[PDB]
Length: 293
Ligand SMILES: [Mg+2]
Image (tube, rainbow, N blue to C red; front, side, top):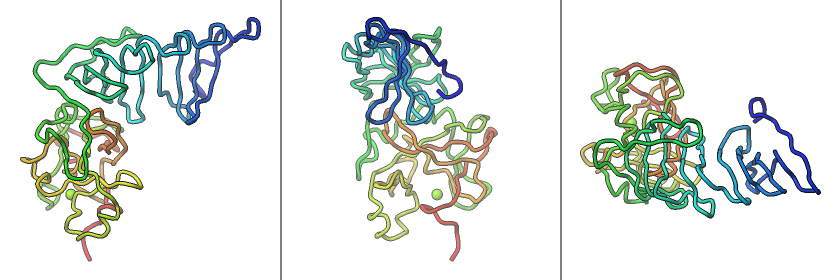
């Protein structure tokens, strides 16, 4: 909120704040809230360590109250009537994907997805979202990978990804399979997720490189990998990000993603507009060298 976000006024009654106020959190979050008698009461917006919106909702007696929005840097969000304690815990909470349409609506506990059914965000009317369950039995839950288990439901595809990309034989290369866009999309579009087993950089750096075909560093402490049963689509297709080939002229980029089912992972995001049936590629780099030598 440096250039948009309405800057506001407040007034004091007996040394107590009324109206708009700003408070900084321990982690650095900046809350712009509404105050009634020096306590949070009314609409509030929170911003991260920069000017980006990470929360929109309202407080009652210093506690978050009704329908609140939580925004992730990747474009996803979590929305629902909050607990009496201000926590995203209820039966009507939803994770909404970056298209602000596809959603997983259901039971959440403190922001964790316990039972999210596929749904579509049908309207907001600009306060509260309205969801409609999609036809079917598609349910999802927070299921973060370990060092050996990639997923409790390896053949259950991510529904957002499945409408956007598919795996087929690559034409502009000889790396075998490739990842292709199903639809035409503009730049900055999340297309696919890179989930996998969670291992250590020391593990990847010290083992035979032939085991590192599908390795991707997630942060300083961990590498995401799609090891050998799972490198086969018949054994794993919950996510398909590892199928995107590497190139010196990529049309996509790896990026951090907060996924309600997979947890902290990376995703594939377009660099430019991409056409239907166009192959998606990411740049060579530290965790995937160019051919040769
Ligand atoms: Mg590859």
